[PDB]
């Protein structure tokens, strides 16, 4: 009959008999062991009259990546080629993008971009810089990259999905936008370095910076902190703040460990109306709101101290089986711990919880000292006429650990190690909470109302440089010598909704960056995780970037003024973070101090006043797939990673699978978490901000396939010995 | 390794009428002309060889 | 081999078809030739000898062939 | 305001019939994040707070017009038998009615609900002329 389809334009095309193998041959033009006949046949597509060729490409690529495995894990590049082809088609239709101008100058009025780029550069040098971005490098992605890219990484209407960009103009567009306020004498020759860095996957960038660049809504932070004390106005203010701020790509570290107990009301009335149970519903509903910029749904994380008179009787709120009185399972609860509570449990002391507001000089003392703190803690155990609740530490700890193993989302922060290693000065402004991902810390001051400048909240900004995509670490300085400079222009460029949030972030200029890939570099080195050959193997080069990044910061900010709050920092005293670590033995992974650059700290005290924070270690879960790297510092679940999300079922592969088929190790094959603990502790020798660690077990290696209670407790304790950072998912295995 | 085994291996014997092949005529009409042409060509080549 | 290759044109010089039209079948017959001839003793007449240009055919063809611290 | 005022012997007549439909977002993003269903949870949790001066527990009452594009499909939120997606039974819901809607029903006209913000000069006109 009339075997016609709806072509790219809409006219009735031919029967698609021939010219269909042309595209798949174009894809597999230089691959191997790819079954063109199978993928052309295993599509299992319906051939009814009235189909659109765009839908045909969609379904053939949905069926292409479906049939993949370690047997023939080769044509994932074919899927990526088909993906970028369909993307360039839905962008223009042809296979020849404009010369960076007909696309930019023609789409600038579309409102998707910011109406200042064209007014910030010249048309003459525009074409000169245009002949540097041949799109031939765009054919080097993976399906796991283009998938998330088309999902939510670049500019597009979230209701129409009509993409208006291209993954090639992305890098140069962001690099050109980040370098606006600069002298017009070297920016043209300076943007090329950053473009070559980002295109070769040597430096990685998050969604908050790639999902929000060159966009009218100038918001680029990644996490924010806020704490609320005992006051109604403060609660209203922080509720308005969380409602307003989460609407632009935010991360929340809410803390409310200072509200009230359940004792009484002085001027006549109920104590707290059942305490924190109804109050936390407000925050839970607040964080459950509009998407964080239009990409995903945010999720905050609350905290409260263990000595609260409202004990872990409220901690069950994350459990599943229970009445609907208090079971709000929408947050990431947090609890504080110090060096003495575990000691009181080891000795067997029954901890006696009490009311925060009913006593004076206790909450701040929980972070300040030990003599007065212990004296007060015993003096109340002595003071009869104040209402408390005593309980053996064993039952409380067992309930907490059971809730953690059940829900798998309860985090714990080590406040003792949260000050003894921070670059800040723990004498005038200590830390009090952590963001939802548990990798950062900064001082925070409460507020009575949003319009007042008395309060102050802080934020940060992330980035990542690859570890494994390089050949020699020597050039890293130059790489750093660019990115931080670029990151500088990021701070004084973005906007701030909360009027009080501007001052603190303009003063401290806190900034931390990390790394994406960890397993590929370790395999290229030639050591595994189980035996312990990596316990000091990473101290040869990785122990140098943390000390040489400060060199780049000093060389790039020795003339850019000073930090308005630099005096409030331990590093401002004259001691570099080269030995200020409270290790267990300081020789568990003993190695000679490779780079003791005292000239660095000399010049720093001389005139070096850079950003407050230096670096961090974020997991970068949504990111790190653009370059097809390993998700965070944790090893992959297997050789091929089968992942699931709202889109579908993806299958990513680790790099160098052909030449290193059996060179990595699956986390299913590493039962001893002591190796992971030793690794993160070796990283503790040079970590700046924090690390987002994680542990995982396997019920197939226990007595009766049931979880233990002291073995994992022993693991927690030996993690509390050396390498003491935040906690995360229990990460069981069904 | 000869008829002592391979001729003894011919135990897959099967009656051709013992199977059911009826869906052919129901799945032969609605097909392109060239498809039927090449199908009959292949069948003729097989039977002649 | 060349005679069979030339034969595999008349049953195809009328229209395309899913799976294989001319190149896939040519690669297949070349691979079959190169794999079968190297079982009686003869120099390889065709270079490459790469993977099977159509592997799913192997799925049907006679799988059962014959602390205080 | 509702969090601060209800704490002293108050009575609330909250009205939120002018928030958004579920159409779209101009500058790029989702329309309303499922509309009023998640937004009303905030008010429900707010009114569920400390006693109104220390005598009893207050309870607000929301309102919304019938012509809202989010139709009475959300009115079931006060029903008992149903999933926990949207069944917040803690308020006194309210709906607006004029002299013409009942007339449109008597005549048999199938009312066509629409979005408040997508059109101009309609919400105030619902009370003016
Ligand atoms: N013969 C065909 N008839 C209908 N659709 C086809 C055919 N071949 C392929 N398709 C699918 C895959 C193509 O990406 C899509 C149409 O893209 P398109 O580039 O316009 O096809 P085309 O290459 O034959 O036209 P043109 O040569 O003008 O570029 O439809
Ligand atoms: N209406 C209320 N009745 C009883 N407690 C309330 C009420 N509203 C809030 N609360 C909780 C949260 C408040 O932080 C705390 C009361 O402290 P506050 O807000 O300073 O008011 P207040 O000064 O009248 O009481 P207090 O003298 O105990 O601080 O009790
Ligand atoms: N749904 C999420 C997940 C993480 N985050 C934040 O992003 C960081 C970790 O996520 P990520 O680095 O994998 O995000 P991407 O850069 O990969 O897009 C943490 O600081 C989180 O607070 C978020 O805002 N929303
Ligand atoms: Mg074409
Ligand atoms: Mg008070």
Image (spheres, coloured by chain):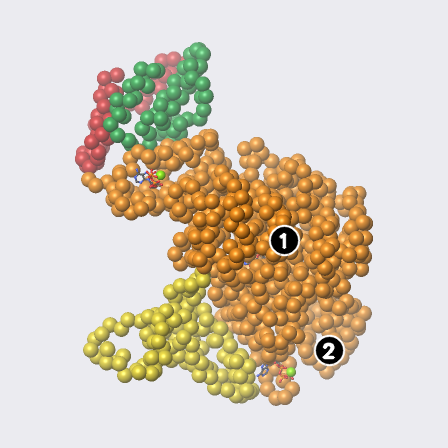
Chain colours: A orange, B red, C green, D yellow
Q: For the point 48% across and 57% down, which residue is it? A: A113
| Chain for numbered disc 2 | A
Q: For the point 42% across and 17% down, which residue is it? A: C46
Residue D91 picture location, percent across and down: 43, 79
Q: Which of marks 2 and 1 is nearer the N terminus?
A: 1
Residue A68 picture location, percent across and down: 45, 39
Q: Is residue A226 above or below residue A729?
A: below
Q: In this view, does A215 lie to the left or right of A304?
A: left
Name which quarter of the figure residue A458 lies in: bottom right
Q: In this view, does A607 lie to the left or right of A331?
A: right
**Residue for badge 1:** A183
Query: In the rendered view of the protein, which quadrant contains the N terminus of chain A?
Result: top left
The alpha-carbon separation of the residues under discs 2 and 1 comes to: 56 Å
Query: Considering the numbered disc 2 on the image, is that residue within a helix, a strand or a loop?
Result: loop
Image region (quadrant) for ligand 3: bottom right
Q: In this view, does A335 lie to the left or right of A370?
A: left
Q: For the point 79% across and 72% down, which residue is it? A: A372
- Residue A309 in view here: no
Mark 2 or 1, closer to the camera: 1
**Residue for badge 2:** A360
Residue A643 picture location, percent across and down: 49, 48
Out of B14 and A467, give the one closest to the viewer. Answer: A467
- Name, please, the residue furthest toward the front: A124
């Amino acid at each position: 009959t009339d075997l016609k389809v709806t072509k790219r334009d809409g006219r009735l095309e031919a029967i698609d008999l021939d010219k269909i193998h042309r595209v798949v041959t174009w894809a597999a033009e230089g691959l191997e062991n790819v079954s063109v006949s199978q993928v052309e046949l295993k599509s299992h597509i319906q051939f009814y009259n009235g189909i659109r060729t765009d839908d045909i490409h969609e379904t053939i690529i949905k069926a292409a990546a479906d049939l993949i495995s370690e047997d023939t894990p080769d044509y994932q590049y074919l899927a990526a080629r088909l993906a970028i082809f369909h993307l360039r088609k839905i962008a223009y239709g042809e296979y020849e993008p404009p010369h960076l101008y007909n696309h930019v100058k023609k789409l600038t009025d579309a409102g998707k971009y910011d109406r200042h780029i064209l007014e910030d550069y010249s048309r003459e040098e525009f074409d000169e810089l245009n002949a540097y971005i041949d799109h031939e490098r765009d054919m080097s992605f993976s399906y796991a990259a283009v998938k998330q890219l088309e999902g939510k990484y670049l500019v597009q209407n979230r209701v129409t999905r009509q993409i208006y960009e291209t993954p090639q103009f992305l890098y140069v567009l962001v690099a050109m936008c980040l370098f606006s306020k600069y002298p017009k004498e070297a920016r043209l020759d300076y943007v090329k370095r950053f473009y070559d860095a980002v295109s070769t996957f040597k430096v990685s960038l998050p969604t908050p910076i790639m999902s929000g660049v060159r966009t009218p809504t100038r918001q680029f932070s990644s996490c924010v902190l806020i704490e609320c004390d005992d006051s109604l106005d403060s609660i209203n203010a922080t509720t308005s703040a969380i409602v307003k701020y989460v609407s632009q790509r935010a991360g929340i570290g809410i803390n409310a460990g200072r509200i009230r107990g359940l004792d009484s009301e002085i001027r006549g009335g109920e104590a707290r109306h059942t305490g924190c149970i109804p109050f936390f519903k407000m925050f839970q509903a607040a964080v459950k709101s509009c998407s964080q910029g239009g990409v995903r749904g945010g999720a905050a994380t609350l905290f409260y101290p263990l000595w609260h008179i409202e004990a872990e009787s409220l901690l069950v709120l994350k459990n599943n089986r229970g009445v609907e009185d208090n079971r709000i399972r929408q947050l990431d609860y947090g609890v504080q711990i110090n060096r003495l509570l575990y000691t009181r449990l080891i000795k067997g002391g029954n901890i006696t919880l009490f009311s925060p507001n009913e006593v004076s000089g206790l909450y701040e003392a929980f972070f300040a000292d030990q003599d007065e703190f212990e004296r007060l803690y015993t003096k109340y155990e002595q003071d009869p006429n104040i209402r408390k609740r005593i309980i053996p530490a064993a039952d409380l700890f067992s309930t907490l650990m059971q809730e953690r193993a059940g829900t798998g989302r309860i985090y714990i922060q080590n406040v003792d190690h949260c000050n003894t290693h921070s670059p800040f000065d723990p004498r005038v402004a200590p830390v009090h909470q952590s963001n939802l991902c548990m990798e950062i810390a900064l001082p925070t001051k409460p507020l009575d109302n949003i319009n007042d400048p008395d309060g102050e909240i802080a934020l940060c900004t992330l980035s990542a440089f690859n570890l494994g995509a390089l050949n020699s670490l020597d050039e890293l300085e130059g790489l750093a010598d660019l990115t931080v400079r670029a990151l500088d222009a990021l701070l004084d460029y973005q906007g701030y909704p909360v009027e009080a949030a501007r001052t603190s972030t303009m003063d401290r200029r806190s900034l931390g960056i990390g790394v994406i890939n960890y397993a590929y570099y370790l395999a290229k080195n030639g050591v595994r995780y189980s035996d312990g050959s990596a316990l000091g193997l990473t101290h040869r080069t990785f122990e140098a970037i943390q000390y040489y990044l400060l060199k780049a910061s000093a060389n790039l900010a020795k003339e850019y003024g000073a930090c308005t709050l630099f005096n409030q920092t331990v590093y401002s005293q004259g001691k570099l973070p080269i030995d200020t670590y409270k290790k267990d033995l300081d020789a568990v992974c003993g190695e000679p101090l490779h780079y003791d650059w005292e000239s660095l700290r000399a010049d720093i005290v001389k005139y070096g006043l850079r950003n407050s924070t230096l670096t961090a270690l974020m997991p970068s879960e949504t990111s790190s797939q653009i370059a097809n790297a390993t998700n965070g510092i944790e090893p992959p679940r297997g050789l091929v990673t089968v992942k699931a999300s709202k889109d579908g079922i993806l299958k990513q592969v680790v790099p160098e699978f052909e030449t290193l088929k059996n060179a990595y190790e699956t986390l299913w094959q590493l039962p001893g978490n002591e190796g992971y603990l030793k690794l993160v502790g070796v990283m503790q020798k040079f970590v700046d901000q924090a690390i987002s660690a994680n542990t995982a077990y396997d019920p197939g290696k226990f007595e009766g396939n049931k979880v233990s209670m002291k073995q994992m407790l022993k693991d927690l304790l030996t993690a509390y010995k050396y390498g003491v950072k935040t906690l995360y998912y229990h990460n069981t295995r069904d | 390794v000869f008829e002592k085994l391979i001729e003894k291996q011919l135990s897959f014997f099967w009656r051709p009428e013992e199977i059911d092949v009826s869906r052919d005529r129901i799945d032969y009409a609605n097909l392109p002309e060239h498809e039927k042409h090449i199908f009959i060509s292949n069948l003729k080549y097989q039977t002649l060889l | 081999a060349e005679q069979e290759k030339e034969w595999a044109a008349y049953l195809f010089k009328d229209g395309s078809m899913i799976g294989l039209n001319k190149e896939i079948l040519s690669q297949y017959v070349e691979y079959i030739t190169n794999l079968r001839m190297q079982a009686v003793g003869l120099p390889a007449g065709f270079e490459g000898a790469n993977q099977n240009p159509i592997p799913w055919i192997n799925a049907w063809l006679s799988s059962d062939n014959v602390d205080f611290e």
